[PDB]
Amino acid sequence: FKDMFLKYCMESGLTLIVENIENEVDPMMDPVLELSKEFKLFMTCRLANPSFSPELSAKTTIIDFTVTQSGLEQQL
Amino acid sequence: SNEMASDLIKQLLEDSELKNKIFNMEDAENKGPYQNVFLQEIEYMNALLSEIVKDLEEIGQGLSGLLTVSENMEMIIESIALSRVPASWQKLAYPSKRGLQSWLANLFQRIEQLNIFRDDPYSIPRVVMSRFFNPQSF
Amino acid sequence: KTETVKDLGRTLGVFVVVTNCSDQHRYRDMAKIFKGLVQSGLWGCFDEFNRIDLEVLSVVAMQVESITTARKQHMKKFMFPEEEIEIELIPTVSYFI
Amino acid sequence: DQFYIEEIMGAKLLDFREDIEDITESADKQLKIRTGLDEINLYWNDMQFQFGIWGKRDVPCMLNGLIVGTILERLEEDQLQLSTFNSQRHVTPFKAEVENLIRTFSDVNDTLDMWVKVQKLWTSLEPVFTGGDIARQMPLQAKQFQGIDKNWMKIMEKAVETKKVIPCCQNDMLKDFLPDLNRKLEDCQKMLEAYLEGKRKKFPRFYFVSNPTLLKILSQGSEPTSIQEDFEKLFDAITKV
Amino acid sequence: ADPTSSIDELAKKKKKFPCEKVSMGEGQERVARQVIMKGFVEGGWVILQNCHLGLKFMEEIETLVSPINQIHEDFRLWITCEQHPKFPLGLLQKTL
């Protein structure tokens, strides 16, 4: 993933979805973050109550998909 | 029929590449007559089996090698399809009838024990003591 | 532990064999061992028997249960699992882990 | 390929800079990819060929590649680069050569793998049948191993005459024999476990003895000498007699 | 405490056939798999034992019990284990 899935997505745009963010970042992930013009990338974390660094909030937008009990009432 | 002919050369003769092509070491014709008795059967089968293997390979190069079709080619292919070795195999010697099934095997065991009778490391002085084609001479 | 087991073996006058089980073990060697035990009549002490595959533990359960039943009825000739040839037994055997 | 700057300028430079620029950056990346193909072909045609041979203790010689790790990994990223190029948009010329190169490499790979695994099997089986007593006790699979040895020596001499592993692997007759030899060796292992159950029955205490040291124990060739160093791992405390 | 006797008495009163049993371990993955395939094609009952150990066969089970591979009716599965964390919840999310 660190070498292939990068150069494939970076040169052909396969969208490179990542699903195991746990506040640890391979340093190589960042300079790719910030050159095919057909490439997007959506990444997400798993465990709630994150402790993201101040700068990791400066780069990417943060959305909480915690549902709740309140939302649970409308589905019920 | 055709393949196993060449395949049994690689399967049987590969163990008897010496025996179908062996020559006695020259001690020469020695004192013992029974030794010279043994000798003349040894050269019987060895010449015979040498003739047999020629037939096996010249058919082989007829099938998977470059050679025109001769008369003996059709006779041997119908014989190998008939599974009976033709009259030439019967004219040279008299083994069992079913030329394909376990017929090499009867000759196989005979030629194994024959090689032991010639050179056992105990039959070098021609002292050895079903595989005989002429017991009355013995 | 192993010293007390070996001392009981020594004072009984029997020969004890200690082995060291590990995660790289397989049941073929355990079966070889148990067959040697039941054939000779020596004692066996599998030190660190726990640090082994749960899988191996399971199949060893069947093997040891077979030989335990075999010794129970005081039968001279018995049948060992996974091994077709019938095999004998000598009473003064034992297992320790 | 034959004109002057007056002509290239008669072609309007600013108006056709779109086209000339597509072609310009395309050709720059084309020089990049063209070197990427050229140097890799130059290296791959002059690859290293050093092999470690087990020994000369017979007429032929059997070798193995102690660099095949390097060979295989460089092959992997080679096909990686070649597929990456072919996938990028600016690779019009290479399709003719790159495909043939990839094909040769891909075939030599799996041929090498099958060959080397069968070599491992045979290198395991050799010293078993070097011994005389066991070869006499089991004559059948001994001569079966002789047949596989003759086939093996033919393949080895074909390798030696090739002198280049890529054509040696491009040989087609090879691929047929290897799996048949594998299944035959499996039959041999079945018979060998039969013989192992046969060998275990003799003298229980040998159960706490491994295989090769047991073969050594059974190959005494002498009354005192052979066993005088083995009493310890056969009894409890006796060492000399 | 074990309901294995009870479960077997149950397999004798409503069901007509004695259940098949495999104790979890080595030489048991393929053994448990082949007896499960036999239960798939017939519709018998299988009793796994000691699932607190030999957990590598557990993650396979959830893939086996699926609508894709069709199973004959009357085939039930009974699992027994103990308190072992690091137990993937594949079946823990889908079981009784």
Image (cartoon, coloured by chain):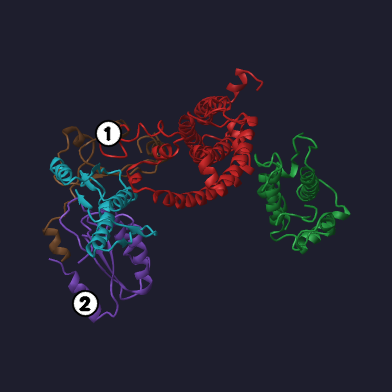
Residue D18 in percent (x, y) is at: 50, 31
Q: Residue furthest front?
A: B31
Crowdedness near tag 1: few (<14), some (14–19) or many (≥20) residues, C-alpha within 10 Å: few
Pick whichever, D46 or E12, lies toward us: E12
Residue D69: x, y in percent? 45, 32
Q: Is residue D114 above or below residue B95?
A: above
- Mark 2: which secondary structure? helix
Q: Colour of chain D?
A: red
Which chain identifier belongs to the purple chain? E
- Mark drawn on residue E10: 2
Q: What color was chain C assigned in the picture?
A: cyan
| Residue E80 left/right relative to A15 | left
Circle 2 Cα neighbour tier, 10 Å, few/some/many (<14 / 14–19 / ≥20): some
**Which residue bears the numbered disc 1?**
A26
Q: Nearer the viewer, residue D97 or C88?
A: C88
Chain A visual colour? brown
Which hue belongs to chain B? Answer: green
Q: Nearer the viewer, mark 2 or mark 1?
A: 2
Residue at 69% over, 51% down: B8
Q: Are marks 2 and 1 in contact (CB under 8 Å)?
A: no
Image location of residue B86, percent across then percent down: 82, 59
Can residue D133 be seen in the rendering of this structure? Answer: yes
Whether residue B3 is visible, yes or no, is no
**Left or right: C38, with D4 as reference point:** left
